[PDB]
Amino acid sequence: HEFAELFYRTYIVTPDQAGFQLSIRRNLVWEGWTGEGLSGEKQEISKRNILQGLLDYTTLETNSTELIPVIQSGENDEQFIDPSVLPAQTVKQGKDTFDTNFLKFSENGEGFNLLMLAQTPSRLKKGSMTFTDSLDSRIALKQLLISVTKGGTTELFALDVNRDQYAAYTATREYNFRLMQLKFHTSLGLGEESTTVAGAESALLKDLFDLGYRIELDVKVDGEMNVENGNGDTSLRALRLARVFDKEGKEIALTDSRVSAALSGLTVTGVGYSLEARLTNINQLEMGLLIDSDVQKQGFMIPTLPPLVIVKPAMVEDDKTYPRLEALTTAYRIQQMRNNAVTTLLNRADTLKSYLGVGVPHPIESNLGLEGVGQYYVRPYYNEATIDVLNDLNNLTSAAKQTDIQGLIVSKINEMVYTADQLTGYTAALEAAFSGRSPKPHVAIGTDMRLPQYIQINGDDRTVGIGYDYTIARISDLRMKDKIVMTFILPNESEPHPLQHGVLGFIPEYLVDFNMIRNQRIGREIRLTPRYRYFNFLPIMLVINVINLEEAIAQRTALDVNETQVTPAS
Amino acid sequence: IESNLGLEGVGQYYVRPYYNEATIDVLNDLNNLTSAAKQTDIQGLIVSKINE
Picture 1 (cartoon, rainbow over the protein chains, first blue to last red):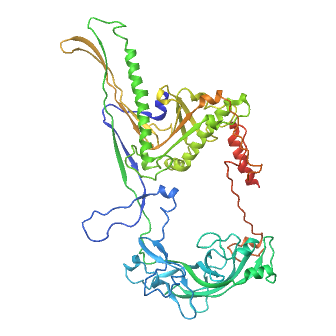
Picture 2: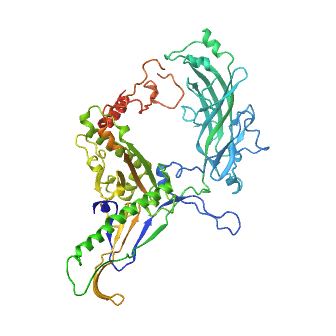
Picture 3: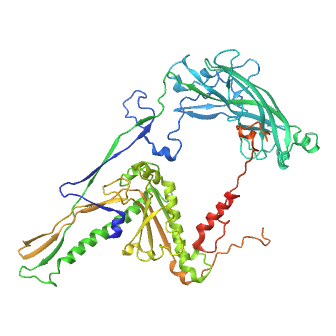
């Protein structure tokens, strides 16, 4: 039957093997190893599939060569800004947790030796930092902390000074051959929407901001750095409010009453800075990211089933007391092809409801209880919706109700397919599974006898959207009362492939006919022993509930007119 | 032009700098008369803003 065929393609099996065994490949990215401590514990192993990095950005992004200042209470505290101004922030590098903060500006003789100040525990366990270690050619200012004060209120500012025209250290030959210099003179602006580091719009500049004005800060800062031994220093040399502009794009002098009054009482002082520095590793002390692969294999077995019988006396061959064989074949075909398939599909739907909620996808290999091995390769996903036809219809003329309903259903279906494709990554899975073809995701559509008189469209182009294929199969079972089911299918593979919804293990069976003495009674019997089962692979399923379609076609429906508020109420 | 020494960019020595942003709250901001033309109206609304 069509409905059974569409969701689970028949995969014939020669009747001498107990089932079919699947070998699926995988490629893994995973960092570090075992090797910690000294005990009898079993430890653990971390494994991340690379396809997670295809959607999320953190699986494949990691930094092991950054040099982040680390606070230690009582011996490296002086080089850091006062904790009272800004509390320490915790930043994680690899497996070490530590607190960091901006470096205090040097006055006249204070420095900082970045190599021996960025000692994280991971580097500590390896010994003293090797003299051969060198800093990368790129050194740059990451953030400047700038304090604006007026009357006693302090608001800290985190300006992203990185990626500015002169935030990058340059090569210079005046003193040494690997001494890097920073020469940073420009104007730093604070726009009319600029926010503080403490959240929300600033309040110390309300006067200028109300008139839409901005402020240019004259920032001119010099520093030097030696990438051979980490000796370097930085000292801010000026910060001053310089000009004022308006929203028309022209300068406004400070001699006017408004500008002078608004700028009065403002004091700006240098607070700190941060550095983007990567240790150019030459010693190879880094694991980076590893790429390994292992194999997973699953077993599937094909059972036997209770038999169907026909009885008659062994003097008898008729049509009524002995119905022809055709009836037996039809009963077999029905119980095989429709009832079991529908019930297993509904159980699959209920299980997917229970395990994954509604509308919330889980990552790759996030469950091991879900039947099937497609879960190893794509995100599991589930979603529900309800179409209230009495509420969702906007006609304009009673003679076009059919087209309106028809398009309403098609639009919801198309949107659902698009959302599933977006949240699942299914298209990327297809493009990875086969190279040389770019197969459009083929979508199955199944329902009872009622709806397929509305899913088609004759007058509007959209059926599943331009660029998707589809196939509708109608099933007579009453359990499918006004229900819509969708799944992703590829009708090009005749082998169990972990990217199709399901397979139907089929074993051909031939009837047996003999005389049998059943408890001292004599009679002729006919047997048919079926052998099959339905296996589910893909953990992606969509179900749509449609109700109240009956009333809308006959009940007066016209518009939900949004009288969008032009009469005094707001 | 050339008024901004801040921010990275060399092309700002040739063209004025400009940046603006608009958001579309589709739900209450759209025109339909028939459910048969929902998607076309939605498509037109976004294309209009892209033009502007």
